[PDB]
Image (cartoon, coloured by chain):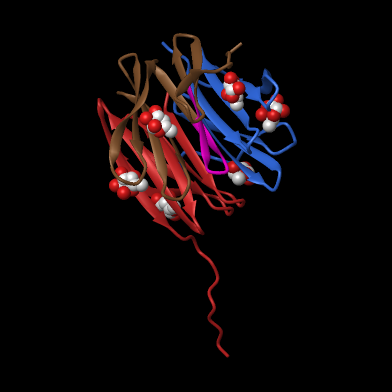
Chain colours: A brown, B red, C blue
Amino acid sequence: SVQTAATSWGTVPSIRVYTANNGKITERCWDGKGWYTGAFNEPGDNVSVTSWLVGSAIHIRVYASTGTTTTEWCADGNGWTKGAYTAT
Amino acid sequence: SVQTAATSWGTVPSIRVYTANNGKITERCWDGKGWYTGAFNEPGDNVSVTSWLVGSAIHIRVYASTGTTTTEWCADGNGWTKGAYTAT
Amino acid sequence: SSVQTAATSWGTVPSIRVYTANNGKITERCWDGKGWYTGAFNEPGDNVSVTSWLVGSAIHIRVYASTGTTTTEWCADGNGWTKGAYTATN
Ligand SMILES: C[C@@H]1O[C@@H](O)[C@@H](O)[C@H](O)[C@@H]1O
Ligand SMILES: C[C@@H]1O[C@@H](O)[C@@H](O)[C@H](O)[C@@H]1O
Ligand SMILES: C[C@@H]1O[C@@H](O)[C@@H](O)[C@H](O)[C@@H]1O
Ligand SMILES: C[C@@H]1O[C@@H](O)[C@@H](O)[C@H](O)[C@@H]1O
Ligand SMILES: C[C@@H]1O[C@@H](O)[C@@H](O)[C@H](O)[C@@H]1O
Ligand SMILES: C[C@@H]1O[C@H](O)[C@@H](O)[C@H](O)[C@@H]1O
């Protein structure tokens, strides 16, 4: 079975749903006007997500794992960047 | 092992915990006064959840997956509060 | 297979907590603005979820750790991590 993770923000709301399927994580997006495919596409067998607002600006962190390696992906308004997270 | 997803809201808080076990997802609930089994019962091998407030009203989305098929389930509302009635 | 994670965050700094189940043990990595560090949480589990809420400026965290058909709730309220009253069934 695929594995999903979800976040949301605001009152509209916006929702982002990440799905790990066959070693790849993809993103479906809701901003009030229908589901669409988001920009996020990265390798992983497992996904988690959290997000927070700074005023009206959304920040998202997606944790993608394959084997024992977890990579953090960051959305801070300009598209996705690798974060500093290490699992240790 | 069973797989869970959790969400919470307010400052009481209210918590909802969803558990996928043997292809069924069930819901346990906390609103300050003990754990109880919720109405949510739907098929799934994997679950995620998110929730947001609009004023006092909570809105919940549960993402239930079996195979490659993810179904979104939706609920919302206002929990129990004392009303204006007086016997005057 | 792959490790399994859960994440929560609060405030605007923000603070982030990332729980990882790896080979039957869940550990915690923490961000409070100044670098990632290993947290106090360390308990058994193959699967993990988490939620948290603020009461004013006080964070409260609940981690749901599952092994087999047993899910244990762990509570962070300022007294270390304690076992909560959650059970999966009546
Ligand atoms: C916030 C939205 O709520 C309903 O409109 C659903 O049909 C959508 O899929 C979304 O969850
Ligand atoms: C907040 C951002 O919203 C859309 O632009 C998506 O395409 C990105 O992947 C991200 O989720
Ligand atoms: C909130 C922080 O944002 C960026 O600085 C990342 O590189 C960190 O790992 C963290 O996610
Ligand atoms: C909120 C707390 O932050 C750090 O003190 C961690 O070591 C604890 O495990 C908890 O996450
Ligand atoms: C919010 C509540 O906090 C404690 O009372 C736990 O024992 C409960 O199970 C619940 O998590
Ligand atoms: C918010 C709602 O609380 C109720 O008591 C539950 O039975 C519903 O399934 C839902 O979680």
* Figure check: C17 above or below B43: above
Q: Position of residue A10 (x, y in %)?
A: 48, 46
**Quarter of the displayed picture in which ligand 5 can be seen:** top right
In this rendered view, identify the residue nearer to me: C90 or A28.
A28
Which residue appears at 59% of the width and 53% of the height? B32
Which residue appears at 31% of the width and 40% of the height? B72
Which residue appears at 53% of the width and 28% of the height? C7
In this rendered view, identify the residue nearer to me: B39 or C88.
B39
Specify whether residue C6 is painted magenta: no
Instruction: Name, please, the residue furthest toward the right.
Output: C79
Quadrant housing residue C53: top right
Instruction: Name, please, the residue furthest toward the bottom.
Output: B88
Q: Is residue A85 visible?
A: yes
| In the image: residue C48, left or right of residue B39 | right
Quadrant housing residue A25: top left
Q: Which residues are magenta?
A: A50-62
Instruction: Name, please, the residue furthest toward the front.
Output: A78
Q: Is residue A5 visible?
A: no
Quadrant housing residue A84: top right
* Figure check: C1 above or below C49: above
Q: Position of residue C80 (x, y in %)?
A: 73, 31
Secondary structure character of the magenta stretch overall:
strand
Q: Position of residue A50 (x, y in %)?
A: 51, 32
